[PDB]
Length: 187
Image (cartoon, rainbow, N blue to C red; front, side):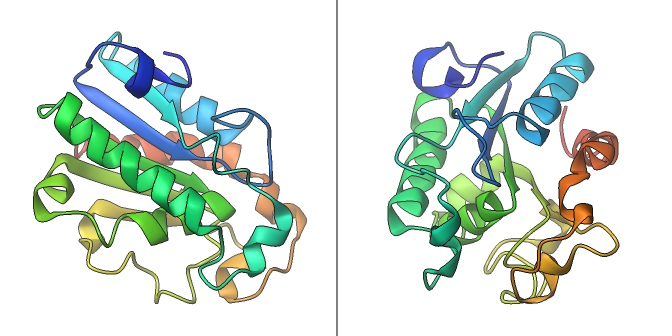
């Protein structure tokens, strides 16, 4: 899988739409985005398309202090990608993902999607979620049993302010658990 597969590749049975954080470069970032994509593909080999939220989402650090914790352009771009999966590949199983500010993108884009698009989203994994406290530990109007907010012990960004600590940068160790959780929701 690549980083622009939903826009530029054939439909796959599983489509991973991921919004990066800690302003890593590229559509997918460098750390947990590619890691999650790679491990999903190893569990469902050849059946996974991977898609980063970009390039209109620029993942700027200052964007964390906008009202929704990211730019409206980023939220719009993510929503367009979920809707594209729905029209281009109506049978694909969508997995949403975000890290840090990328979780704020997912918190903003998913609530407004149609019921039918939400039916296609089988799970959303949010690493180091900067909006955990602000949205009450869930994505608004999206099922909690399809939501996995992963907060490391000591990662204070999940407590309502942007206090960065070393624990915010260790989510590579949580990818195996994230993919185990996704497997219970994917076929």
